[PDB]
Length: 284
Ligand SMILES: COc1cc2nccc(Oc3ccc(NC(=O)NC4CC4)c(Cl)c3)c2cc1C(N)=O
Image 1 (cartoon, rainbow, N blue to C red):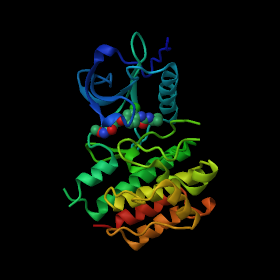
Image 2: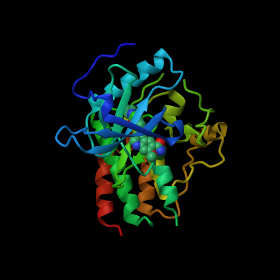
Image 3: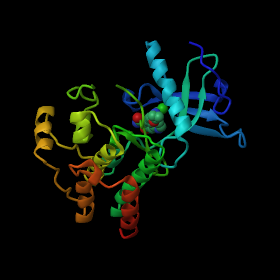
Image 4: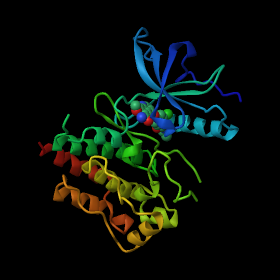
């Protein structure tokens, strides 16, 4: 275990004041932290940051995984609407990967806590637009998410949506095994991805369809009370979820377009961004 230094991102450990943990192990031992002078221009400023690290009893393969994650972020590059890499502590101690902090939790929790401040109809659509922008970027950089969901969209102090866990490789996951927090991850998967193991930017758009439904149900659980075996039957039968209560016909049509049985007929993020752009413009 000897990691190579990268002076682009390298940060001294003495510049990193660690803090309370974040988000229930959902992202693999993350903590709140305070980085003293990330920006070498203003070196006397603290910045609130998130810091992922390896677990108490992590394996040699877990380290391999965490490095790939770090390098992935390096390559993909910066965008407002994704979790950006800020730095890392690689030398003379455990690996710390420092990323942008998102004060107001994930999107599911964010929406649930703000059920009836209010979110204007505009806020919700604005929020959906932002995720589409973030996904357009990732798509432009050949990056397939594979698990796009409100659970993996974080929200900042400034209410900016930041996509997380995009990329994060692996290779036949168990459909039946749940998120121990209380979630069945297969319900976001497109049929081609679910059945045939074929992940594409189109399969992500299917998931974005489900994410839209999540938004306009203020953190609603999709296919509630439907076990795995039943979900298979439903998707096979061409079943699609009902329109949310607070959700226009235009937006529901967008969901349905995202849930088009034929992958190539689904709209691209590029298109979704443009449509959402226009729709945000006309909303209270
Ligand atoms: C308070 O809520 C959170 C804020 C967070 N802010 C930043 C990063 C977080 O966690 C993450 C979330 C994701 C990643 N990693 C990636 O996004 N990696 C990308 C390349 C695959 C990392 Cl390091 C840390 C946060 C998690 C929570 C929370 N309640 O769970």
